[PDB]
Image (cartoon, coloured by chain):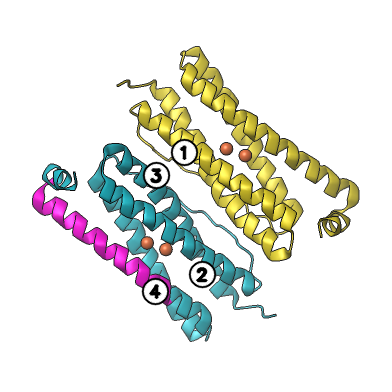
Chain colours: A yellow, B cyan
């Protein structure tokens, strides 16, 4: 019914890619956390991978509605941590860069008056910023407490 | 309780990577098929992504049990098709190469007498070969019938 802007489509595909990587990374990390007996951390990672799945859905829906083609695009490795701090750091690196990409896209969607795409991305960004926030606190505590002291209060 | 062979672990991580890519690709393709009104094709792609998820689980379980670390490793783009034939071809390219990697790994697991890893991979290979087979038939029919004639008998 309506072919959308092609740079918007190109942005949506870039963001979709970000989500797929986030999905795979939190799936792995969640399983590693669980293997260690860190219920709380596994719980949040697991639910996060579910959310990112949901974002990915929204993105694909939107590309298809705009008569665009899903088109990844080199996702890019992929930094599975070897300890909790490392894992959370890679996660936060992924999230921050994702948020950036979202902010640029939202800008461009608005310039070209794709308010539907813009508003969808804004809703998603809000989600991103909450997890970013959560992540920055955990890493703060590991810093302040020390990784071992931090873990043991999880257990 | 038991640190496993490190080349086996390295192989398991390579195969895990293959699964993650397969998961992301069939998730996308399944959604594209569905957007076109191809219930049967979407149904099989969707269920396939579920299976590959299950393989990924088995792999991560096994790496963790062998005191190995999940470690991807450049997944590699990623070839989303633009029509059904193209999509199925990319899928089959992915599957065949995956099967190959499995066969090498199974060989090596057996040489070093990791029968548990070997047997797990054999079970997985059997799954791979069935979908490969299914895929080779669909592509045969598209060839014999022509893509349009093929589709319309789906609908
Ligand atoms: Fe997201
Ligand atoms: Fe997020
Ligand atoms: Fe598989
Ligand atoms: Fe398969």
Residue ID at (30%, 57%):
B92
Pick whichever of labels 2 and 4 is earlier in the sequence.
2
Q: Can residue B121 be seen in this view?
A: yes
Q: Are marks 2 and 1 on the same chain?
A: no
Q: Are marks 2 and 4 on the same chain?
A: yes
Q: In this view, does A2 lie to the left or right of A40?
A: left
Residue B11 vertical placement versus A84 (above, below): below
**Chain hosting mark 2:** B
Pick whichever of labels 2 and 3 is earlier in the sequence.
2
Gap between marks 2 and 4 measured at Cα:
11 Å
The kind of secondary structure element at disc 2 is: helix
Q: What residue sits right under mark 1 in the picture?
A: A57
In the image, A154 versus A98, the foreground residue is A154
Mark 4 and mark 3 in contact? Answer it, CB < 8 Å. Answer: no
Disc nearest the viewer among 1 and 3: 1
Mark 4 lies within 8 Å of ligand 3 (Cβ measured) = no
How many neighbours does mark 4 have within 10 angstroms: few (below 14), some (14-19), or many (20 or more)? some
Gap between marks 2 and 3 measured at Cα:
26 Å
Residue A143 vertical placement versus B1 (above, below): above
Location of residue B150 in the rendering, given as x and y in whole percent from the top left corner = 14, 48
Mark 1 and mark 4 in contact? Answer it, CB < 8 Å. Answer: no
The kind of secondary structure element at disc 4 is: helix
In which quadrant of the rendered image does the N terminus of chain B lie?
A: bottom right
Dividing the image into four quarters, tell me where ligand 3 lies.
Answer: bottom left
How many neighbours does mark 2 have within 10 angstroms: few (below 14), some (14-19), or many (20 or more)? many
**Chain hosting mark 1:** A
Q: What residue sits right under mark 3 in the picture?
A: B28
Q: What residue sits right under mark 4 in the picture?
A: B103
Give the magenta range: B122-146
Q: Is residue B86 left or right of residue A15?
A: left
Q: Is residue B128 magenta?
A: yes
């Amino acid at each position: 019914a309506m072919k959308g802007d092609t740079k918007v489509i190109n942005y949506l595909n870039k963001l979709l890619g970000n989500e797929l990587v986030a999905i795979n990374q939190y799936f792995l990390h969640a399983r590693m956390f669980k293997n260690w007996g860190l219920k709380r951390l596994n719980d949040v990672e697991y639910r996060e991978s579910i959310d990112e799945m949901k974002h990915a859905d929204r993105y694909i829906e939107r590309i298809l509605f705009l008569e665009g083609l899903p088109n990844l695009q080199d996702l890019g490795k992929l930094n599975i941590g070897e300890d909790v701090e490392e894992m959370l750091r890679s996660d936060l690196a992924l999230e921050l860069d994702g948020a950036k990409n979202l902010r640029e896209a939202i800008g461009y969607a608005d310039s070209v008056r794709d308010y539907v795409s813009r508003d969808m991305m804004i809703e998603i960004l809000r989600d991103e910023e909450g997890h970013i926030d959560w992540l920055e606190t955990e890493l703060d505590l590991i810093q302040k407490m020390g990784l071992q002291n931090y873990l043991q209060a999880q257990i």
